[PDB]
Image: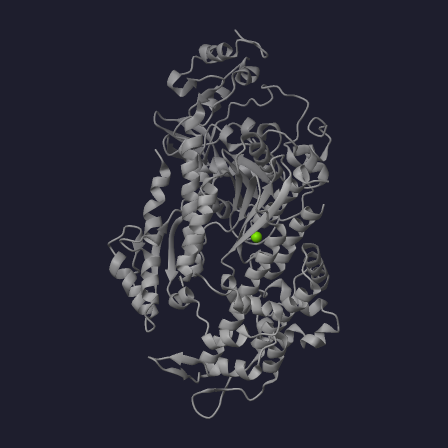
């Protein structure tokens, strides 16, 4: 029994190694400490100082450099006793200060223990190296075990959720959030892995469920500067079960796919995996039928300078992808078509618009153009017209307009983006019919999306994501405001103002004003931003109009202020595509293409704007969550460099500050963070009472009784005692 076998990998890899002695005595030392900053500029930095003097209301401790210093007892970051270094739940700590929190996580991570609980959260820190804790053998261990009965692990949370589902007959959720490269997607896959094993029917459906992923990963993931396999879309996966607890189906909901990546990537980044998969792995035959060449031959793939990922065979991955397409069930038919779309996109990208005779766009070469048409199975002359000579309504008048180079290009870009996003939608719908169950009994849904985004530049997509995050954070706080209550002040009240600033109807918030502006064809970024400032500058406490910038505005989010830039918002909100282009493509010969333009469910939004659609999909998701028993996983990146063995304090604390763990902590820290079992308190603290005593509670008053700790510091409740913050350490800080 791996859990009892101190030699198993379970022990090696998931527990703090245990010695031969369990005695309270080894742990002794008289030397107290505090966490201080040897330089206050940079506050996430701390060193341990041995407190050598105590004023009546402050301490005076000894720097690592030997110099003594003074401190207020109330500003003191007390270091928990060493016995606590490495505990499995931060809730077990006496001193719940941030450095204290950072220290426990670091001590663990130093042992390659990447998972740790903090109350209701599972904290997961990317090790940036492979740890073999996801084997079937590791799966097996988690089966039916309580949270408290096994080491922290994604497997654990998953079991607890599945058991809760069976036991309470209630749907569940796991919300997996954090920065890019934190391991959200990785962990998401382990949840499904685990579920598939503990509950699959020893299989077709399960294989399909599993193969859908790689499918969506090829089309929605890409190499970026923070992650070789970045998810450029958010997702909510519903794992469906029958009443007996068996997997009966699945559904995927996708959000905010980064369509622009198809047309542009920053230096070092790559376009979506698939482009490269197609090009590297296509038979030397399709290459031709598709008019393929190499990546360098394509504007959409030859700009970033990076066309490869180390440790990655685009060719092999392509094998993998088509393989998944087969399992799920896409006909070879379907598959050439997908491939063609892809090919087409690439061609559309190579079309060069020139300066003809005056001011209007022309096409000297038609090569790329016909390559494009060919593959899509559209009429090249139509396309051509549709691209440079779109007919535009101007009254009762329908007039062709000759676009200049630029405009033509952008329009071109719009087509590619529509093609891409639509195809993605279609992929998702298709997968769903195969997987999805009408008649499901229960479900476990997993949300894999980013946490708050504060980048160098924040645009419309950032506001969207941050908006979702305000809602999830308030959902958390609201949840915690119940869980905490039912031991045996609702802070979510707190996010309302920001939320309203974004989504409010009357008075209107940012999105409503954006929608309003969107009706006017001649509106501009300036008109827009000016409208925003008119309604909210010095008028809404969560808004800030900048001192000098004329194109940005600030929103005070849960995680702090985020400055956004307004450019292109109107256009992003409308996500326009010339009608002629729709017409052209409404006629494709190709069977798939036609669905993309012919199916209102794919080809359109309602027509609502992009904002209105985001808001509504967010509200549905939240409604879904609202009916589940939720579980929270906070994935942390250890540094910004993708390196193992480098847990950067500032990097870490920041995330803890923004993803709500620190708030969670400091909340309960105002109450009774510790609430130990009676028997449990007695066994290590007996040292009137001996270890395994049966009048537990009594044995528990007893110890507090000898030591005669202050009563308001502790509280007698059935089964457990609670200890206000710091009580434990001092209790722990006392002679035998
Ligand atoms: Mg991901």
Residue drawn at x 67%, y 43% is 131
Residue drawn at x 70%, y 68% is 280
Q: Residue 302 or 612: which is nearer the viewer?
A: 612
- Where residue 670 appears, x then y in whole percent? 38, 30
Residue 402, quarter of picture: bottom left
What color scheme is it? one colour
Residue at far right of view: 284
Q: Is residue 519 above or below residue 464?
A: below
Residue at far front of view: 439
Decide if residue 322 is in sight here: yes
Residue 342, quarter of picture: bottom right
Residue 657, quarter of picture: top left
Residue drawn at x 61%, y 42% is 191
Q: Residue 125 or 207: which is nearer the viewer?
A: 207
Q: Is residue 24 above or below residue 208?
A: above
Residue at far top of view: 688
- Where residue 462 appears, x then y in whole percent? 44, 57
Q: Residue 438 or 291: which is nearer the viewer?
A: 438
- Where residue 189 appears, x then y in whole percent? 62, 47
- Where residue 295 appears, x then y in whole percent? 65, 72
- Asked whether, in this view, residue 53 is left or right of residue 680, the answer is left
| Total residue callouts | 0
| Quadrant where the image shows the N terminus | top right
Decide if residue 223 is in sight here: no
| Quadrant where the image shows the C terminus | top right
- Asked whether, in this view, residue 548 is left or right of residue 682, the answer is left
Q: Residue 453 or 352: which is nearer the viewer?
A: 352
């Amino acid at each position: 029994n791996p859990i009892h076998d101190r030699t198993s990998d379970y022990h090696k890899y998931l527990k703090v190694k245990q010695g031969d002695s369990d005695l309270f005595k080894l742990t002794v030392s008289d030397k107290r400490y505090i966490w201080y900053n040897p330089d206050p500029k940079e506050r996430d930095s701390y060193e341990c100082g041995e407190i050598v003097s105590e004023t009546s209301d402050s301490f005076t401790f000894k720097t690592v450099d030997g110099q003594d210093r003074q401190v207020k007892k109330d500003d003191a970051n007390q270091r928990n006793p060493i016995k606590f270094d490495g505990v499995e739940d931060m809730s077990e700590l006496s001193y719940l200060n941030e450095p204290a929190v950072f220290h426990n996580l670091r001590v663990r991570y130093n042992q390659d223990l990447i998972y740790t609980y903090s109350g209701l959260f599972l904290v997961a820190v990317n090790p940036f190296k492979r740890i073999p804790i996801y084997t079937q053998e590791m799966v097996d261990i988690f089966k039916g075990r309580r949270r408290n009965e096994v080491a922290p692990h994604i497997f654990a949370i998953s079991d607890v959720a599945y058991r809760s589902m069976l036991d309470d007959r209630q749907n569940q959720s796991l919300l997996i959030t954090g920065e890019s490269g934190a391991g959200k997607t990785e962990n998401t896959k382990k949840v499904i892995q685990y579920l598939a094993s503990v509950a699959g029917r020893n299989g077709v459906l399960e294989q399909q469920i599993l193969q859908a992923n790689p499918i969506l990963e090829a089309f929605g993931n890409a190499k970026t500067t923070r992650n070789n396999n970045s998810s450029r879309f958010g997702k909510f996966i519903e794992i469906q079960f029958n009443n007996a607890g068996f997997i009966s189906g699945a559904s995927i909901q996708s959000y905010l796919l980064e369509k622009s990546r198809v047309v542009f990537q920053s230096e070092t980044e790559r376009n979506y995996h698939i482009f490269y998969q197609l090009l590297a792995g296509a038979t030397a035959e399709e290459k031709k039928a598709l008019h393929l060449a190499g990546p360098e031959s394509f504007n959409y793939l030859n700009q970033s300078g990076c066309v490869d990922i180390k440790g990655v065979s685009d060719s092999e991955e392509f094998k993998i992808t088509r393989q998944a397409m087969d399992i799920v069930g896409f006909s070879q038919e379907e598959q050439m078509s997908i491939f063609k779309i892809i090919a087409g996109i690439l061609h559309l990208g190579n079309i060069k618009f020139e300066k003809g005779a005056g001011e209007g766009a022309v096409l000297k070469d038609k090569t790329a153009l016909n390559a494009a048409s060919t593959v899509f199975g559209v009429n090249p002359s139509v396309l051509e017209k549709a691209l440079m000579e779109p007919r535009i309504l101007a009254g009762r008048d329908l007039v062709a307009q000759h676009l200049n180079v630029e405009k033509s290009s952008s329009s071109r870009d719009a087509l590619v983006k529509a093609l891409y996003g639509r195809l993605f939608l279609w992929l998702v719908k298709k997968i769903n019919n195969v997987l999805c169950q009408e008649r499901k009994a229960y479900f476990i849904g997993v949300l894999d999306i980013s946490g708050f985004e504060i980048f160098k530049v924040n645009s419309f997509e950032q506001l969207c994501i941050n908006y979702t995050n305000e809602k999830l954070q308030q959902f958390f706080n609201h949840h915690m405001f119940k869980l905490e209550q039912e031991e045996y002040i609702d802070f979510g009240l707190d996010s309302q103002a920001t939320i309203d600033l974004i989504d409010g109807r009357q008075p209107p918030g940012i999105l409503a004003l954006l929608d309003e502006q969107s009706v006017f064809p001649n509106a501009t970024d300036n008109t827009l931003i000016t409208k925003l400032h008119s309604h909210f500058s010095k008028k809404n406490a969560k808004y800030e109009e900048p001192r000098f910038s004329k194109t940005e505005f600030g929103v005070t989010h849960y995680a702090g202020q985020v400055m956004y830039e307004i450019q292109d918002w109107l256009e992003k909100n409308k996500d326009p595509l010339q009608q002629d282009l729709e017409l052209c493509f409404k006629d494709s010969s190709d069977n798939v293409v036609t669905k993309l333009f012919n199916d209102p469910n794919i080809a359109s939004r309602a027509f609502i704007t992009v904002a209105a659609q985001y808001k509504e999909q967010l509200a549905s998701l939240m409604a879904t969550l609202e009916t589940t028993n939720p579980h929270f996983v906070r994935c942390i990146i250890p540094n910004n460099k993708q390196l193992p063995a480098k847990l950067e304090d500032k990097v870490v604390l920041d995330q803890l500050r923004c993803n709500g763990v620190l708030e969670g902590i400091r909340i309960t820290r105002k109450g009774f963070p510790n609430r130990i079992i009676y028997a449990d308190f007695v066994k290590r603290y007996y040292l009137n009472v001996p270890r395994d005593a049966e009048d537990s509670q009594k044995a528990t008053d007893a110890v507090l009784k000898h030591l005669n700790i202050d009563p308001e510091q502790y509280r007698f409740g059935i089964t457990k005692i609670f200890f206000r913050a710091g009580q434990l350490a001092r209790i722990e800080e006392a002679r035998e």
